[PDB]
Length: 275
Length: 243
Length: 91
Image (cartoon, rainbow over all chains, first blue to last red; front, side, top):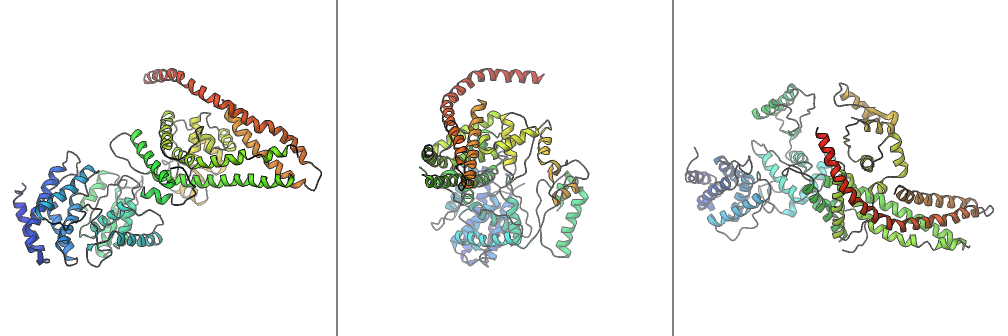
């Protein structure tokens, strides 16, 4: 089974210990971070259960996700203040535990929880608005992964979307508060070694367009399976095989957008699993 | 609201009672919020779409109506200069025609809120029942009542967007007499920024649209073999297609 | 009921049809004899037509609230008939 909640606290201390070799000025902060991460985990697991939503399923893999998500930000970021690191930690905490959260009652519940945790383990008055909308971290504007300015980001997206609008398919849209937060979310996903993000967007939200965009910013070939009523598994197999052979033997760097419509049978989805 | 605002950024409008742009956007939100709340059942599967297309209908409809209001206002101003040149016994009644000139300001007051209803009919109503449409209309009218936009109290969607020449043309093909079936046909034709989905058990509609486009009418079905190619031929040379 | 909304739109289309007829002849028969007078006796007939609209708008404000008074009784009839059709449909 799972370990302790006190072994988990201890195990991730050693995880933070290793990554705080890169910020030696906060070597004394590894334990309350490890205790906070585990607290956040224990609480998310408790507050958001499979009784509300099926995908509400937490495990120490989240912890490992968070701890590594923290390192990668440090290893490629500006030399860090304590106010930086907790916000750096808080960003990952949001992306790991709360992106999956539906609706708003539960989403606000986590905002309060995150606040409750910092106050209990890392007591500072230097924190700001910890809501995801207010902490925006990016490597689009800086060479180092750093917290960016809301005004600086919106304008950067605006100049790049027109370009993407001109260079690629011509579709005009309104760039808005939700969309900036989401652009960074896809960006982090498409940056990590294994990058798999599934977007749950109703329809016309723009989820398919943003994906094409952020992929273009990251310099990814956007492959979209050309399926139809009279498409066989063999067709999809071919679409997949090529995209695989190009990725290794041509070093292509493709982004495969699969819509729910594209999965025509059981096997199609099984192929996606094996991948 | 962020999205609505940038879509109505273009400003045909003129001062009203109370902001004017701020009011319009707040109505549409409060209508979309009321539409899904009353009509749709099931827990939060569906979200904003009609809203975008409802705004896009309004922009296309206000532009079409304000340019036609200013066109009729120009037709009575050109007749004002021609009667003043002449001045005899009957012509001074014609000059009096400030009742119409006075009437224009009241007509322009309501055109923004009249376009609100027309756009809502085209977008939200297409698939609603006789009673389902009327009842939403009331909720829209009382929303138009809360906000300081003026609407026509004696308003009729048919007469407002259908022209008597077209209304005749439709029936000539063989559209049914009913008000419901008129509104439906108006919804299909009037707005074509989007492909229309016609649902009718009796494929009496598949002939109506065939009579209207005649030779140009090429009929297909998603089930036939040659569908894949026959559509590529239909698209290349401007053929009007029903699937 | 049918002619109320029919002649509302028809007379207004004929008011726009006669305004066009007046402007066509005023520009053609300004150098000719006083023909415009032959359309002005049709414009004298329009004094019934312009005010026919006023006659019909006045009786509309009397007809509409009576139409809405008659919807209620038929609603009472109407609501039972669907429940009956529903039942016969269900067989």
